[PDB]
Length: 116
Ligand SMILES: [Zn+2]
Image 1 (tube, rainbow, N blue to C red):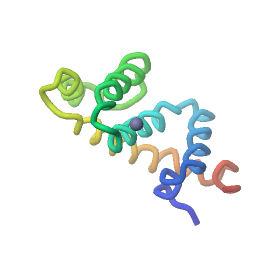
Image 2 (image 1 turned 90 degrees about the vertical axis):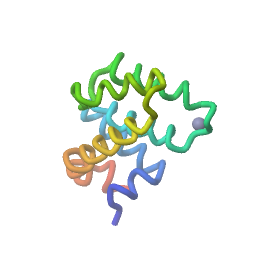
Image 3 (image 1 turned 90 degrees about the horizontal axis):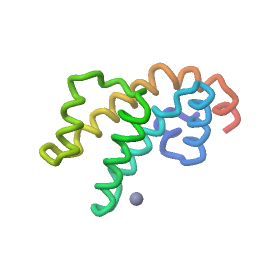
């Protein structure tokens, strides 16, 4: 019996969850979670590109993540180099709880979960 942690940890399972999110027309939430998981495990030399891609694909070219304005300053301050990339790790925890509480319960009754 798979749980949400098992879904995200297996790449096959996670691709099926992402397909579900595209059917819910909200694949930017899993994509942003996937981007910060890359940044968390990446070589130090790809970090600059990865951070700029996170702030452009999300927060600029798309506007689907829910931070509003309080933490948005922290993002800009991490892009310039004052603060660190820990702001993205906290936003990833908030997006994880969102996927877990309001999208995973719908996912476990779809065939993208039940046939795994
Ligand atoms: Zn990499």
